[PDB]
Length: 105
Image (tube, rainbow, N blue to C red; front, side, top):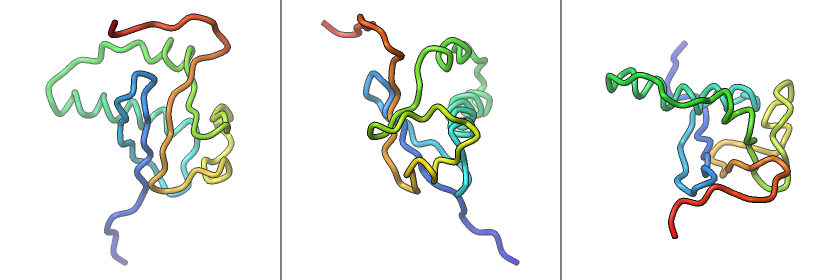
């Protein structure tokens, strides 16, 4: 047939604030999202001649993806099931903690 533009733009309002437009399949999952978020900075760097220098291991193993009360933890669960659709606003969250890493001030 004809393959035009398929997928969705999932926004990742990083904890800090700066949101990152991630792309995924119309039927992506929490996992993919992560992979994408990574393939967004990774692929980018690669195309921009850059070597990875972000411990996604800890990051992923430290923060999660949130939207609106719905904790995006399950990877075997499609986002569409979480209520996340194309052109949505998702942000990161910090596991049950107390303090937080400041930036300004």
